[PDB]
Amino acid sequence: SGFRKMAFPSGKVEGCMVQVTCGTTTLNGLWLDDVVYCPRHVICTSEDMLNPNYEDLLIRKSNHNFLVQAGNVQLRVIGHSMQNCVLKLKVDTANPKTPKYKFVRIQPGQTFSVLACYNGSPSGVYQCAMRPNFTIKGSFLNGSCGSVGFNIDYDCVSFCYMHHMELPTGVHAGTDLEGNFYGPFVDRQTAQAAGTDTTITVNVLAWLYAAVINGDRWFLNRFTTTLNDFNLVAMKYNYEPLTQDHVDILGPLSAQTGIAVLDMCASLKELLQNGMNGRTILGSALLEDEFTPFDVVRQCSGVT
Amino acid sequence: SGFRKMAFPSGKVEGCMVQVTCGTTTLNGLWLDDVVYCPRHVICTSEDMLNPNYEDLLIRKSNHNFLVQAGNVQLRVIGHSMQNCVLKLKVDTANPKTPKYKFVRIQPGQTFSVLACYNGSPSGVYQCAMRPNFTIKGSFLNGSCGSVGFNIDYDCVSFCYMHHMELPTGVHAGTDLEGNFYGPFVDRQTAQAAGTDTTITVNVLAWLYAAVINGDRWFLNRFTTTLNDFNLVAMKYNYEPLTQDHVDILGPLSAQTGIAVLDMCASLKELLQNGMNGRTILGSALLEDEFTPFDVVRQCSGVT
Ligand SMILES: CCNc1ccc(C#N)cn1
Ligand SMILES: CCNc1ccc(C#N)cn1
View (cartoon, rainbow over the protein chains, first blue to last red):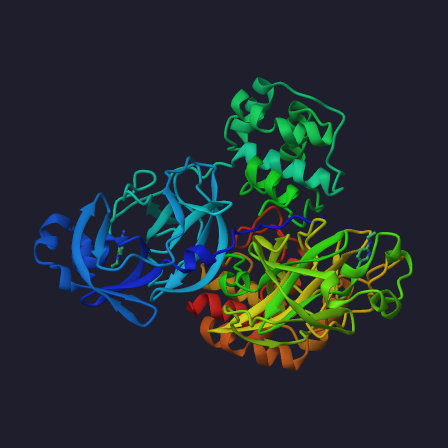
């Protein structure tokens, strides 16, 4: 019993973190096979970040201008290329700790673990979700860029995020490992406001299922609803609209608790219209939306 | 910016997890140098757990009765001893991934990371605190016993917890790595009620400091208080009494924000007497107490 915000074990990713230094700027890189991936803004001065032309700045950068350190050993850079907003440094040594891996671009509402790193050294691991406005709410200080987000299926790491920047509102933006930003963000020291940070309804419902399984049952109500009726309430409270695809995904949790998805919706409707009233669910006074239905099943079944 | 419930990177501990099987019971063990540590209840049938005599049950157990598997390789057990509530299986192979380590017995209110494991395989990592009633609120399914709690200082793992059991209220009890339970709990299938789960006041204050640093400032009030006045309110709200030792520990956070510890107390006093009023602090609608002053400094300074 018990239900925790749980990250994936980090060791497989720890074995891939390196330090990348281009002149004055140090951040983190991800070393898989014989390529190191890092944010392309490692080539910039603070002055360059105002309106950078990355292809222009890169003309002045040679293989020997990219210092890569793995632990306290130097790697030899034998090629480099830009791909969207990331650099790919080819090194002459395959990472001998390279796990099975994939690069995946996640959808908003999907969760992942972040291995926060500084100078190529792991500091901590936490669980994030891709918000509906394509920001994440992380914990990143100066030097954390190039820290990565990932999911693990048994022994395969699916890397889904690389950290690039902090908006003036202190939320976070980054790229997939092809270097494409999530959302509309750009790697420049310019005005970038995030859109509405709506609540990930399907994840809230998953977590309510997680709750009931753990006996935290007080919020269960005598009502049902319909998708359309629920969505009128969702829209009012800045929740994502629930679709039948979300209902289908919650099916296994419905099947476990014998609480029909629309019943759990009608109960969420009451939590939204009446608040917790100083009560808590799984140790939270707000409705938690950074567990996916898959996360709830995984944690409640003890997948390794 | 941003402030997350962060676990230590888990790889150093991942490299120490093994599966221990004694007849029908499988759980996890911790392999350091040439000893595997596990809960002594691995020797018991479900029937044995009603009123077990561990020294009596152990007479019937020889070295070859303890199956230890590290990945998919068997370890040869060349000795075993009981120490309090843990078994120590001597194996003929030093764990080649043994990190620098210590065994520490933590105090209530101290936080640690848990590497939840099943069949010797890591499933997830999360941050816990030793509660004032010597329980932890974990996420542990059947098979998770022998999962460990730890802190890391640079490259030294301080192991502080091994998971043994779940109370009927679904909170968790375990031992240090000398096999001594935290709190009054015993490894038996018997009535064990936890005491008052009071709030760890010094940790709440640390987290309020973490908040102000991140600009989440609305709760800052025009008041100060005294330790004695604050403690009258603490006692009412089932908070731990604040001592000068706690004030001393919060000194560095006081020094950063220019908010005197007693000012932050007077502000906590108002959050306690008036609630959040539907407002949030660092994404929480309750006052978070599983960050220590050390955690806040560590996370806010990016220690690796
Ligand atoms: C002056 C530093 N400002 C920065 C740094 C990195 C990024 C990105 N991506 C944007 N602005
Ligand atoms: C029937 C299983 N019940 C158990 C198992 C482990 C412990 C401990 N420690 C207590 N009860």
